[PDB]
Image (cartoon, rainbow over all chains, first blue to last red; front, side):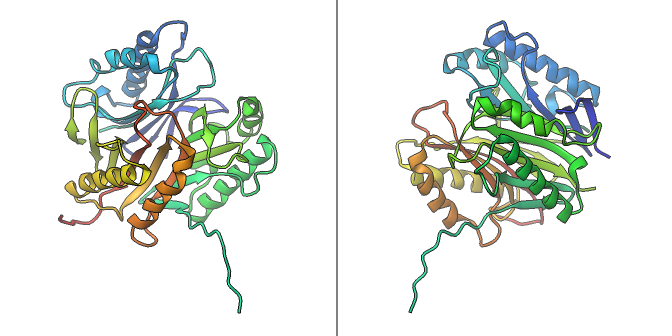
Length: 115
Length: 115
Length: 120
């Protein structure tokens, strides 16, 4: 009784297992912009996915952040550090990575809870 | 007498915690072939591992795919995109990475359910 | 409800969801040391975090290991092999990665169980 969302042959965007939510690699739908813009797009899409299963921004457990360029780290954090409800930031791990599309400045992978 | 010198690797292959399955990084047993062959080997090993604990290919939650070479992306997907039952692909995040053994074309890290 | 530990705007060091423990990216507090030193520092901080919630190093489920330099692989594994009770080491996946601070030789990301009522 795994529930899946936005499913194609290649992937589900999201899978729910009991009360645990898995969200696969998230990138900006419009990767033409800067790190701040792409970060915001990804976080907003995460908001939308979470709301669709009865979760929310305060229920995130872990985020893996794959960052394309070191120079973008401050801009990533500018958006991220203002985002989560007070005292409810998830665990986080950010490193540099080579992503499939050279336009992507960042990719996130998420585990969350659903009450 | 005889003295034996070996390289011995004792791998934590899987850990089960209630109804969630964590699989250690998986690579091809025989990494001499192309991306298609290596991808097939790893997915087949995942079938065997999941079978052994009462899970299956339709119960995968997340797969992190670490691809060694950009040129192998299409070949990875050629196999992957035909693998999963309809509506049952896991969440996925693929990026390029330098792997421990230069022979490996891909490594996969799996979380699955056993219901 | 989720319980979080060592929380700032940027991150919680640890989040507990029922009996599953998530610990975020762990790097050495003092990164001037070699791979063995940094690996020990990281595993000790993981130990402290786990025990604070009633888990322990025999209850880890997965560790993602991001290694900065190929020549450090043997040193990482030397400590790893000295650390965990026989047969109870967690699943792992190690690859080479560029980390944010060039001084960091390794970074680990952890999922663990919190089973029993073990006091530390």
